[PDB]
Amino acid sequence: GLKEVMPTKINLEGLVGDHAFSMEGVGEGNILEGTQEVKISVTKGAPLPFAFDIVSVAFNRAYTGYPEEISDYFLQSFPEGFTYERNIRYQDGGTAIVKSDISLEDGKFIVNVDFKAKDLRRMGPVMQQDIVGMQPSYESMYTNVTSVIGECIIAFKLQTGKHFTYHMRTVYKSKKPVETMPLYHFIQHRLVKTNVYVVQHETAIAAHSTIK
Amino acid sequence: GLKEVMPTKINLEGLVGDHAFSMEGVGEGNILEGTQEVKISVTKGAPLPFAFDIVSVAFNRAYTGYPEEISDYFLQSFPEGFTYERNIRYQDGGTAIVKSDISLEGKFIVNVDFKAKDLRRMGPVMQQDIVGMQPSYESMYTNVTSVIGECIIAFKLQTGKHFTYHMRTVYKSKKPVETMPLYHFIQHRLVKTNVYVVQHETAIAAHSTIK
Image (cartoon, rainbow over all chains, first blue to last red; front, side, top):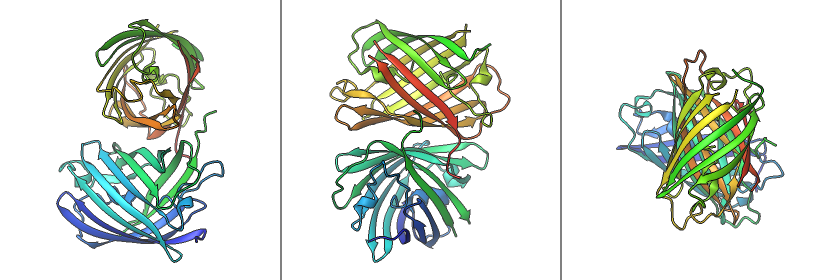
């Protein structure tokens, strides 16, 4: 029950330290090519005390470009869709948890996410808003029983030219059984803000190692 | 003082849990193409009570293929060479610390210390359930005069499941370095080519391939 280019509505609720907030995202993307673009606003708790970029990853693996040769867990989850449970540890010892449900209502991806972070250092890049944006990444993907785990190191480039990184571990779950589970592979990401009351773009392409 | 094809000798001293052991490796590689093959043997403390593969990363970034467009911090460090301090967190809570000196003799003489603890008695490392390493992408970036590499390394288990770890390495040139690299990746694929083992690693530096 999908189309090549798919609209999405994304509702986010969150706590970062003691700060409660709400954001909503709207956009569309190509589920064959692996591109999305979402316009994101705060609907509550603005201004934000922390770098916007920490929620970038929160705002749908349905939008990734899968080669024939690799099993496409995310697509195969539909029309039911999938959820994920994401843990993040920033290099400072701060952590975040991100729970999300990707459902499909009508010809639309409907995403409800709960975002919670704690122990972010007061004088570190996030709380001081010293982040320029994310670098590209390669998320290792692999099956564990009926679920697919993704793991990567995400780097924030800082105003100063240095980087600040985090470990992200995501367990994805198709709501309805997926018959063929994928072999170990990578999804290369590149997520960037293409206009600041924010629009981000992400290109996500799955592939095996290109080393013979 | 280098040569397209460089020989190496590697002396590893280890302690995993309470088990002390010493190992040696001899090999060669291509410092332009980023390839290397090393024959590895235990010289002390055999047989090992854990999977060999955990020391595979311990057995030299001089062996990576670097495009002209990306500053090669490792080639730029010689003739003196470089060191690293590497911290590893296995998914079960086990950790490792690995410290190494890469010096130049036109042979690479490497001396590495490998110390791990908190490995699960019944986990795949102590139970030796590891087939081998998967390919990986190591995020490289500059921090002042050092370069940091960060990766998720994945062990393929006998069952087809995986067991992963997070590796963070601080690489330090012994000599000052003119041009420090911009954010890039090093893609690896390390495999056992014959089991008293021979390993082969390929390492290629590159920027992201998404425009």
